[PDB]
Length: 392
Image (tube, rainbow, N blue to C red; front, top):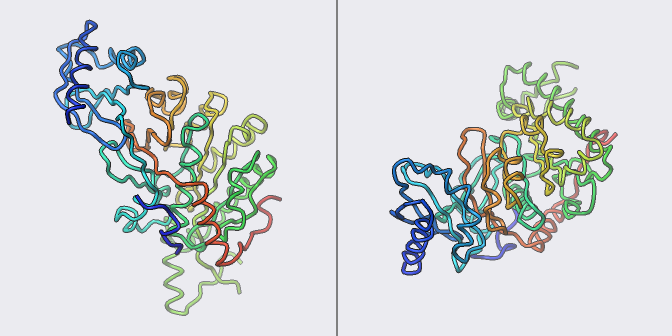
């Protein structure tokens, strides 16, 4: 419902660089040809043809030096270019382009998608808009260093939803233990409860979810339904026929249930003080919340084996890595290097559950002010109908 006008509107140098890359590469016992290259908004991917035997892991363990052999902040070595037998070398463009939220929001890919948890990621290395469905993730983990784009990235996601879902479609439980990052959304009618600030309430909020999931699963059985979607259609049906479905377990009639998106900003604070208990709850939720319409988003900027633990990783299939400071950090996030080779400012590596190959995406950009604009627009439509007990 809010308007898009609340958001701002959107070969020689190459071959020379291709020739220097081939020169710096041959500068070692690495013979390779730059058979091709494709330029995008932020980087340019050079396709190298390694000589017989030359492992693609040989360049990867030399990205730092190589990036230094030329004048670029960093260089990313993609071991496998989908569809081609060549190795990829991503270099930053001299003139970078901003990827505007609005440009992706105004695309068919976002417009056509029926899911209310559709989110804009950004654009792929070739300039194509990338959208994703939180419902299909079905839970996500966002991580990076401080100003690499995680926060802006999360805002892009929520705004995505605020540009397609009515509260009846999606409700949020926002956990911001420390500071006020998510506090900017206070008042949004979508909020199920006030932004959670006490670390103990957080645990309670999660426990609520766990029960809300069993409740929804009970109902789904009574109607012989598999998804939350199938349940709502049964309910829509009952509505069209003015044949209200009375609660089979109990005046009182069943109603449409919204998707609940649980957002935890810097769940590191949640771990470094209530870790064990939280992990316990996250794991249970992440295992069966999908069909029940409950989805987790865990954001952090302190990617450590203490935060992104084994269990956490084992329960959150989809992960997003914004620029990190080291390979270790990246591996903790993606169980694979690469994110320490991004160019900051929204540059990211998406890693879904249905593939081992990560995908580079330049995150959409949203002004802190546009967030306020969008939030003000939503609060004018009315205040949130809080649900009691979530925090108690």
